[PDB]
Image (cartoon, rainbow over all chains, first blue to last red; front, side, top):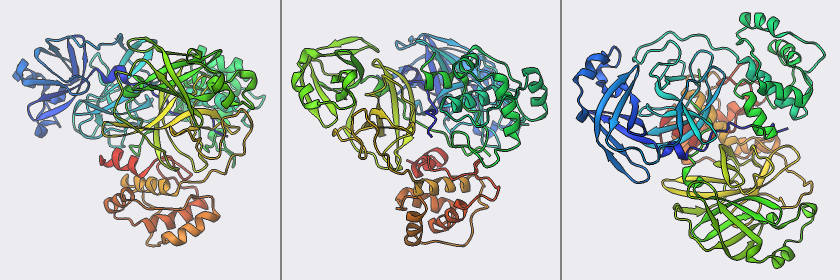
Length: 306
Length: 306
């Protein structure tokens, strides 16, 4: 009756040792300290009166290296001297005179819709919480962020290597959240300006609904499975009309098909039927489709496979 | 629209630094290394072919210090020599020759039904994931644990002090999980033997349902609020007949009533009506009552209280 699924985050210790507090004048938020670089949102430069339409190019011109104060509060505290400052998209790149001795092996990557990542929520340079989210098809995340959380970071892990993919920037009118990749772009079409912004429509993540149906099968809950099949191409035409992402299979889904003996196309048919309603029945304690678990969540948490 | 609530764990770094691998003969699992003590489940002493009815007192007598192999794998790796061994309830207390130099400030506490705690899932002494659960009224948790996860720990955090409350032991018939407190007791009526055990009925955690309804009110979703009230005494008679825990208000629930302007008794009334059905309506994206968020979650995540 319990699926064995939970919202699983990576252990956060490696990333904790990289978090700092960045202060520019009256403004403060979190930064990420890797090697001789500290990354943080560029609106730390912006007066509170100016956040709706800031001119970051002129703000940056007005700054000097001493404009920025960087502190490590956790572990062995440290004051970091800024010796260089640059802007890349919506992020600042501050050069500091000391390399982070706890720099992990890392990369910078962008995450795609439907993919899961771990977030270390920080306030005043101090990690306070960790959670995992799926990047939504409209480039928001359903997170938990308050004033002072900007510069909190999201990441995946491949082995010992941390792949940083997100730095938090803002909350939208519907309560969801968005931020930057570490190439400095904002996810989606968002702007780092405090103004109401058009938000694109969310969608069910089809590949993740398939993963959850396979999780149900692995738990012996298979009432929705029938011989009927919908091809991928036919389902993808259907998805465009019914607020679903288009389905693109992966070896992670294929492993679920093989372990369960249920074809992807059987679950694509099931989804089409279940989207019209569960008819009084339940799947893993839910009466609506679940898209917040990935094929990899299911392989790892239930079958122990990576 | 999105509530701003997520399953939020503590940052796990402090606890990661206390995890070790414990091997006894052919059995391996995880342990918790604090000062010169390593805690682990006592069934590490038990051969696989005897897990269904072990004689732990005789196993313990047969053991020597050299029967146990303890390794720290993460960070500065170490092989820890055992210099004393004892059993307390369902746990072993192994004395080792090195004190953990990363021992945090800590206590041992027991967690109560409805209360949330963070789990660090470990395999072979290596932390692999973190997630949060609430202790169910039947002293199980809806976790994500596989073979080799025993000895994984749960904890709360007050300031800098880690309060260890849970050490993982077993998975039950319905896919849920249970374990020990660090006084050696199993939560609930469970025994650390590989045999089917009666599981008590689960219940809705009334106080957490109240917190969730307040979260909904904080987000503009309050169609279920009426002037009508049910007193705590009347609600608690009803709860015993409808699979709910009895409601016991706390200062943290009182904070939510003040912040929302909605009395506890109004939401007790609502719960009774909602439990008969949402009449095809939704609360924070849900068509059923949610009891996996605590009054403290709502205060901290939505209001930023502590």
